[PDB]
Structure formats: structure tokens, C-alpha cells
């Protein structure tokens, strides 16, 4: 089930069990081993109602995707990860 | 694994991966594409120690279930979803 | 998929769907029916950057594992559980 950082190979980022459908970019409820770079922005957000924060592998700093955070409290999930599929192995 | 709103058929509300057993009403750790109506209440809560908030499909406003939030910090999960099985497709 | 408290048998603590790899002790994103005892500590933490809180079964008080809580905001997950495998069935 593991989806690992493609660059450093060994580092698990998420699992297929975390995949969900909100409507290239995999959306998952939970992820691991990522560092958040900077502050959320809503500029060009692919998911209306959410802001994005760059997320990179904590081991090799590969840009894997973004943490998406809801701007309104009545939305669900309040946060998820949108991950570039080609930056993950399997 | 997708569990969709029975009414609008398009909208995924949770997945079989998210099901867990707290103890008609499916309980899941995580859900999607729900709007929360109102503020939490504990009155007649089906899960003692948790407050509920009505949760409806964001597309068709069909009442799918409730978001349950823990009233005490030492409980696990601190939040979950109780979904009406008859309001979702697959079974 | 259910992993139940071995002692009281009937209480589910987590499911295989919740297992992930942060790298005897199973790590899962989500768990249920556990009571937390005391306050977080980083003393001897098995997971640098996380503090631990003892977690016991809400029904039989068997010690199942620990809740791990991030000491910094930019970590993912912000929390998880580490559960003693021999304290669970399947
Ligand atoms: N490569 C660049 C370069 C400039 C601006 C953006 C990107 C980029 O990937 N995104 C994403 C961030 C994530 C998102 O939701 N929408 C975007 O357009 C930008 O805003
Ligand atoms: N249809 C009605 C009408 C009045 C009050 C409630 C309901 C209802 O479904 N619940 C639920 C909310 C969720 C819960 O935990 N227990 C309930 O009885 C009510 O409190
Ligand atoms: N049985 C004892 C006795 C004293 C201290 C600890 C333990 C114990 O199991 N842990 C764990 C807590 C969880 C952890 O992260 N590291 C540990 O060493 C202790 O700190
Ligand atoms: Zn990496
Ligand atoms: Zn709907
Ligand atoms: Zn037990």
C-alpha cells in the first residue's frame, strides 16, 4: 500500500488507504514525513475554498505537493494533501 | 472503496478505508464534500461523550449524517463521522 | 481489517487501513476507544520531534500504546499512535 518519495525512495509519504475523491494530483486525507514551507496561499488554488502550502519530503526536500487547508470551518475535510503522482513511487 | 451520496450519485462522502467500530449508522474517521449546518449539540447524542453537528452533501444538500466532536480531551478519536447507511451507495 | 484489544476482545483500537511507516510497535494515523493517561513527555521519545502520552483501552484499562504528538507545527502527521502489537488481536 505504501507511496514513497520517488527521489529518496525509502521515505513513505502516504498510503493508498488515504486516497479520497474531492471533485496528475492525488488527494489523500493523511500523509507523513513532509515539511511545510511558508504560509498558506489561495492564489490559483486548484481547490476552491482551500489554501495551499508547499510540502516537501523531510529527507531529501523533493517537492512532493501541497497541504490544502479549508478557509471556512463548515467544509470537510478541514485539510488534505494534494500530491503530484509522478513524485511518488508506485 | 467509494461511498457516494445516494441522491446526487456523483459526490464521494467517505471510503471503506475510513470505516472503524466505535461501539444503521456507519462510523468513519474521515469524510469529504459535507457541509456542516449549525453548532455542536450533545442533546440525545447517540455516542456519549460526543456532540453532533448535522452534515449534508455539499452538492445536493441531502442530510447524510453528523460530525461527532469529543467533549473531553482524553477520548479517542477526538472527531469522527456518523453516516446514515441508507443515504449512501454501495452497501 | 479490525485490530482489537487482546484482553477484552471486543473493543476495536485501530484498523489495518490506518497503518503507515514513519521510519513490536505498530504506527497508525487513527485509533479509537483509548483513554489518555497524563500529559505528553519527550523523555526517551522513540520518535524525535514527538512527545508521548500513555494510551489504554477504555473498557479494560490494558495499556495498548501511546499517542504521539508533534512538538512543532511543520511536521506531518501532527499526531499518530504507536501501539504494542502483542496487545492487539489480529
Ligand atoms: N509552479 C508554480 C509557479 C508559480 C505559481 C504556482 C506554481 C504552482 O505550482 N502553483 C500551484 C500551487 C498549488 C495550487 O493549488 N495551485 C497552483 O497553481 C502556483 O500557484
Ligand atoms: N430528527 C431529529 C429531530 C429532533 C432531534 C434530533 C433528530 C435527530 O436525528 N437527532 C440526532 C442527532 C445526532 C445524534 O447523535 N442523536 C440524535 O438523536 C436529534 O437529536
Ligand atoms: N516502561 C517505562 C518505564 C519508564 C519510562 C518509560 C517506559 C516506557 O515504556 N517508555 C516509553 C514511552 C514511549 C516512548 O516514546 N519512549 C519510551 O521509552 C518510557 O519512557
Ligand atoms: Zn525524499
Ligand atoms: Zn448529494
Ligand atoms: Zn480492552
Image: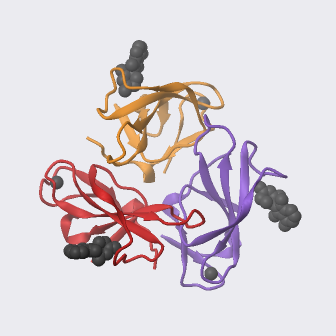
Chain colours: A purple, B orange, C red
x and y percent of residue A13 in the render?
56, 71
Residue C1 appears in the rendering: no
Q: Quadrant of residue C89?
A: bottom left
Q: Is residue A1 left or right of residue B61?
A: left
Q: Quadrant of residue C52?
A: bottom left
Q: Nearer the viewer, residue B44 or A9?
A: B44
Q: Quadrant of ligand 4?
A: bottom right
Residue occupying the point 44% across, 69% down: C50
Residue at point 15% right, 61% down? C6
In the rendered image, residue C10, in percent from the top left (x then y), is placed at: 17, 50
The residue shown at (67%, 38%) is A72
A86 relative to B20, above or below: below
Tell me if I can see residue B52 in this picture: yes
Residue situated in front as seen by the camera: C31 or B69:
B69
Q: Nearer the viewer, residue C1 or A57?
A: A57
Please provide percent x and percent y for residue A67. 66, 59
The tally of labels here is: 0
In this picture, residue A67 sits left or right of residue C61: right
**Which quarter of the rendered picture does the C terminus of chain A lie within?**
bottom right
Along the viewing direction, whichever of A22 and A60 lies nearer the viewer: A60
For image coordinates 40% across by 66% down, the residue present is: C19
Amino acid at each position: 500500500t505504501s507511496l514513497c518519495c520517488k527521489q529518496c525512495q525509502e521515505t513513505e509519504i502516504t498510503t493508498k488507504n488515504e486516497i479520497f475523491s474531492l471533485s496528475e494530483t492525488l488527494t489523500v486525507y493523511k500523509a507523513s514525513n513532509l515539511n511545510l514551507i511558508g504560509r498558506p496561499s489561495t492564489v490559483h488554488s486548484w481547490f476552491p475554498g482551500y489554501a495551499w502550502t508547499i510540502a516537501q519530503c523531510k529527507i531529501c526536500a523533493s517537492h512532493i505537493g501541497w497541504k490544502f487547508t479549508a478557509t471556512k470551518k463548515d467544509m470537510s475535510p478541514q485539510k488534505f494533501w494534494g500530491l503530484t503522482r509522478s513524485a511518488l513511487l508506485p
